[PDB]
Image: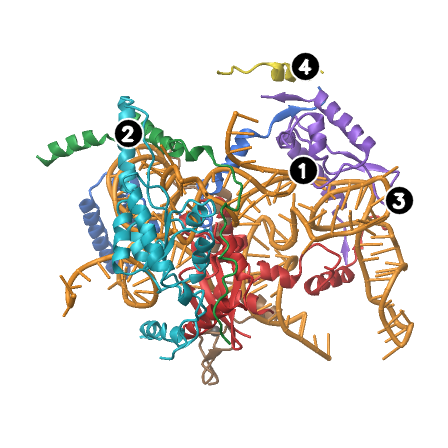
Amino acid sequence: GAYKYLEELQRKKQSDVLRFLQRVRVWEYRQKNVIHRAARPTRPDKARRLGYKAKQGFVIYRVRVRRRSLRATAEERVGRRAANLRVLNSYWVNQDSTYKYFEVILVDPQHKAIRRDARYNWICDPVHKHREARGLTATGKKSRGINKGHKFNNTKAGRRKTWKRQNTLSLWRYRK
Amino acid sequence: AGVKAYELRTKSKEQLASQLVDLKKELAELKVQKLSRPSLPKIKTVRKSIACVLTVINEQQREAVRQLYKGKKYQPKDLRAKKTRALRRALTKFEASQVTEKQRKKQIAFPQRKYAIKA
Amino acid sequence: PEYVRVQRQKKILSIRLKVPPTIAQFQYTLDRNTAAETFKLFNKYRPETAAEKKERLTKEAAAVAEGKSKQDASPKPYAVKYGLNHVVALIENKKAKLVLIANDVDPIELVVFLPALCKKMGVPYAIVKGKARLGTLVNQKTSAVAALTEVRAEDEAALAKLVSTIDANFADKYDEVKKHWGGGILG
Amino acid sequence: VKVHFDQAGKKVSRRNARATRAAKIAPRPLDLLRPVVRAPTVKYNRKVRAGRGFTLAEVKAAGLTAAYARTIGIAVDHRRQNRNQEIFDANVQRLKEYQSKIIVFP
Amino acid sequence: TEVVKKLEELASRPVIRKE
Amino acid sequence: PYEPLIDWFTRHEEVMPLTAVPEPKRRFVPSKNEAKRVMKIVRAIREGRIIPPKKLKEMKXXXXX
Amino acid sequence: KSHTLCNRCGRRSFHVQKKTCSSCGYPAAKTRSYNWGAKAKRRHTTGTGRMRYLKHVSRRFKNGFQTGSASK
RNA sequence: GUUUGACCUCAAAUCAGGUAGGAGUACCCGCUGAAAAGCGGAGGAAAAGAAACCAACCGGGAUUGCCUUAGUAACGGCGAGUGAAGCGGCAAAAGCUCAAAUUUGAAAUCUGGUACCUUCGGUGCCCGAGUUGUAAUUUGGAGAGGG
Ligand SMILES: [Zn+2]
């Protein structure tokens, strides 16, 4: 398939053709709004490996942010704007000195293709409301820093959690 | 000395509307009688009668609307179930029982068996 | 309006700036009569529509329903091939006898390797003008690619001379100017 | 500050769970068939222990597939590795004894 | 043992299978 | 600056494909999934849920009058 | 007067020249509430009013949101 | 051909169907933050969760929580004091899905409308969506083609 070509070509960003397309598209998107709807993913392979499918119930927004993180704030903007949609994920496409550009995949839990088709029906659950608001996305888990490793220690929110471990005292019926 | 519900179920709608007109005239008379009267028990009966007439009329109208909308795969929202927030939403049974074809083949191939240990 | 303003300001900012030579291979494309005969070729090899498919299915199914199991014989379907991953998939065997490539795709990067890929695989590619004209011959809105592998014996001699025609008209004419940086002249 | 006043209560509730789950799982045990596995960490390396799951290769040596063995209630770990002989053999004997004592309904 | 024997007969009971 | 593109890698032509993927069976025989859809329609016609098209034209010829 | 009858809460705390209710926060869609004023939140929660819909909820939850009747 | 049409984009709909808001907020999750307050977002739990793990052993084996590790390691005008984690015992135990090579001998996929029917749906027909990829199969523990 052709996706391996797109990925390997995508890894060479400062190559002449990609910076050409980047330099055209940053001006072209600069013409448009801060937030708008893209007809199709400009980086389809990246959208696939983030989970995009080309059917009804998949909405692609393109979002502009000024230079929390920038990516998570970009997700929060389209989460606030299209509340009926659930945010699947997001990825970088383009940037300027003034703005970075992100391309965000959102999924509607109202469309019957999404309400059926059991690979994706889990996102219809109301526990998946506003994953970007709770940092439950990929960039949210990265900025929370949730993995396995000794490199991963008590960091910020978990720090208050282990402050909570220092703040509360546990007593049994029979004192130990 | 009052109306019955089941007696009003048999009647045509014009009979019910004329009965309503009769009860409203009777109410208008009983107000003129009651502005002289300290306590008139009949007006308390006839307002319940007006209420039952309105009940039967509205019920017949709603069931007629339901019968004309019976076949369609839709309904006016007021005629639908009320239940609550989000029991409207997020799943049907069919939309929850729905499973992929691969896990379907897996459960056909290896279902959870019934066994008894120490035998 | 805004969108008219942008779609007119587009293709100005492109040509004003230096395009890389892996682009502007596009619009160095096939001329009038050769694209015309290419379309006359591929309309001989239209794929089956969903209606025609379902119709033949109902015919043979009513045959088996009577039963009246007539025979078990059909040579093969021959048609154009149009799925992009399927088009790339027909290369690297190789199976693509001819490939048409649309010049206009908005994610151009979907397409840019295909001339070099058919160049190294030796596949007779040709850059066609307009993916809508590809979609018309393949019952889609757009197609952006058009591969063709299997040809009847009635058409095989026309195929080879069309290949030689394209390799004369495309590979000889535009090969050196393909290497050159296009555009760059202001508007 | 927190006091476990419910220590008496939760146990009762837990046994209610151990009742209620058992009601649904009426012939079968509540727990799966776990491996007998020797511990790490030289303080504990003489100690043997209950392990998570056996392996693919061991269940194949028992004479069945792990996909089927999960339906029989045998806990299976892919990411474990069998490196000791006697551990492997004792757990194979354990699997065989478990196979001897089950009766499976069609 | 008794109900063990009964379930052992039931699991030992061949189901009416179809070719 | 700018300079024309070097075609060092294109000019060597591969006489063989990349992958030694074995050819599947279904590329040579009539298509199976077609036939499964055929038998689906056969089961629907045996249940009469689908009318044969000759019978449909017979229906339309009478219904026009 | 400094304040006016609020259209939302009816408290006589709709300030005039600020065009706002100091009590409830009309016309802002979110209601004003302060956690330091926990006693103030106590005076205005659910349960103070009629709960015209909210009374009969859990009873329907006890009945499983049944429909119709059984004539017998 | 000054015509006609494919697209593509962008508008408009008292067009059809849906959905967002607010309240509460004990528990949860994010953001901000002093000498907590605040903000945002959920649920009956939430979060986390199936190793780019821990170890150095006769190795262990998703996550979660309890007891112990332990007031130890470590940190700290090494002052005030701050303050873990591996292992072990227990509770509970459950694992799975994508994205990469073609179905090319037939997009096999789905929304919607309509007609019926046994209606949390089914069947038929028709618009559409979709090859700039929807289905089946395959997630390394491999797997696929065949025989
Ligand atoms: Zn107010």
What is the x, y in percent for residue A128? Answer: 53, 54
> Which chain does red denote in the image?
A
User: How much space separates mark 3 and mark 4, taking CA atoms?
Assistant: 47 Å
**Disc 3 residue type (three-letter):** Val
Q: Which residue is mark 1?
A: D17
Label 1 SS: helix
Q: Colour of chain G?
A: brown
Label 4 SS: helix
Label 2 SS: helix
| G4, C73: nearer the viewer | C73
Q: Which residue is mark 3?
A: D42
> Which chain does cyan denote in the image?
C
> Which chain does orange denote in the image?
H
Q: Which residue is mark 4?
A: E5
Q: Is mark 3 within 8 Å of ligand 1?
A: no
The vertical placement of A98 against C74, above or below, is below
Quadrant in the picture for the N terminus of chain B: top left
What is the x, y in percent for residue C83? Answer: 39, 49
What is the x, y in percent for residue G5? Answer: 44, 77
User: How much space separates mark 3 and mark 2, taking CA atoms?
Assistant: 75 Å
Determine the residue located farthest toward the left in the rendered image. F65
Q: Colour of chain F?
A: green
Quadrant in the picture for the C terminus of chain B: top right
